[PDB]
Image (cartoon, rainbow over all chains, first blue to last red; front, side, top):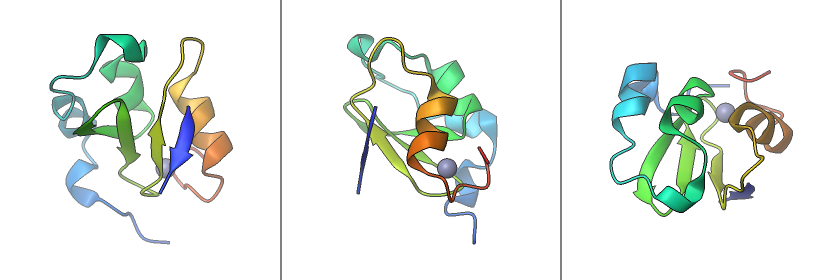
Length: 5
Length: 79
Ligand SMILES: [Zn+2]
């Protein structure tokens, strides 16, 4: 999974 | 630091947020909620009630706890 903001 | 979303402190409230969770995401609401993650209602995008950390593009093989901890080292919940 990839983080996002 | 502060708990970012106390309305999602209950693991049962996190489970209930998983309405229309998509089939391609592979990870289950049960696992994601247990790692402090609730559904934002968009794609496979989840958020932590504790750190406010946002996660998406879940892939088969991911573990909710591991992705959460590895990406958000400041999170008290998975510390
Ligand atoms: Zn967190």
